[PDB]
Figure 1 (cartoon, each protein chain N blue to C red):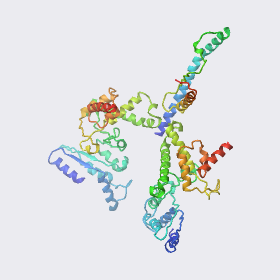
Figure 2 (tube, helix red, strand yellow):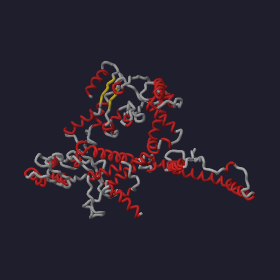
Figure 3 (spheres, one colour):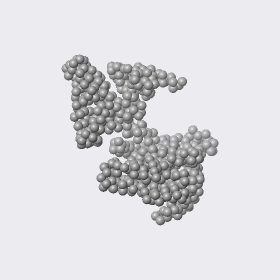
Figure 4 (cartoon, rainbow over the protein chains, first blue to last red):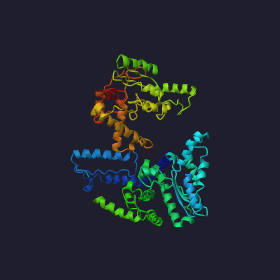
Length: 104
Length: 247
Length: 245
């Protein structure tokens, strides 16, 4: 049982490394888009020096109701990952229950 | 044991009728031989039995044979010493016993009675041309599913039930369904179970296993297959349990 | 053993005193019996000992009984050979003793002295009538925590400490605090290494274990409880550890 467990966890280590590398490859796939987007955005910010009356996605004029969105890892045994994530989430929602934010 | 054999051998040599001798704890026929062989002057063998363990055991077991005048079917309740399945007393009787059936404390501690092991219990009557082709195929599929479960017992116990595949998870749930469905309410074990006994034939258990491992009814709860006579009684117990859940 | 035991029983039966006999290495007595009975022609027995390995040492132990005149509290440092408790020479002593404390080599390999294994260490005096429901209940709770830790040690095997949920994580933190606290610098282990010895009383250690099991001491690290006396001194050691960083 211990030898088969060792073989299985070695297989999961190899598969997890390949999955990490394929996620990195997806990020490098995305980096053309992100670079072109982060340069066109500056091109807009240079043609107009934030001369704007627009974009309802820039209403930071209060902190009335925050929506902390927490992504987490979704499998079994999850390293030591999911507990750390939701722990920081619980600390942050506690701090947002202090201020009275009514967080979703 | 030789007295039982002499009565059976008379009923097979003279009365020309097929007899069914049940010997209980044939391991006593070897252990008493041990206790006398120690004093007798014969040297001790392996773990503590007599030297002529095999020849004495054969002198009992060989006289039980269908001999053209009848047929002595026999079911010896061999005792494995503390489940030492490699000990001389069962190791010599495995050679003589045709349709052996290894009952396991491992599959009894979880309450699955009878404690017969699905894997270890094997018979030389599971050849297809002898037992029926569909029955042989169902037996092969059940044994393979239980073997896959016994091989995934290490992954399940340590790395969690979720860390395996989602087809292999179907095989695990199917193996659970099977290894619970092959429980039986005996008529004589009603005092231990508390529930009445259901005698179920061969074709009915084949028709049950076909629908269980064909994936057609993988929705029933696991306890609905526990201590149940037939697959129709399992379907009825699923309704009973779903009503008792909300009620 | 017989001559020292006669020397003690003369005091317990004629002078009426509460004499002690710290008979050391009972196993050496049984092994001497093994030698002499391998040479005395007596037929061999279990693994190597004399056939009379349960009557000769019976003549040792059963003469150590507290009579109505005086009482004797013998402390017999019986030795398990090759570090297995199934052996017959200590197995026949387990049945005679009543407050057996198994000094398993595990906690000494971990550096926790004394290495008295809290699960194997057991006594017929851990009863409600004898020690009071207070000390008995705390003993039951600490044995509970340590047993839960030892049974999930099979998971603190191949996997890591993280895979435990919050329940098992808290009980492991508490069990580590306890199995560290069960160490003590002896008053005679000033020679080897460590602090001068600290005499810890029953009504004093009961406070420490009530405090640890009550959860009010989660702030302290593990190397703070190690090799300390009372619980106030444990908190002092933690504070000084934080000052020395």
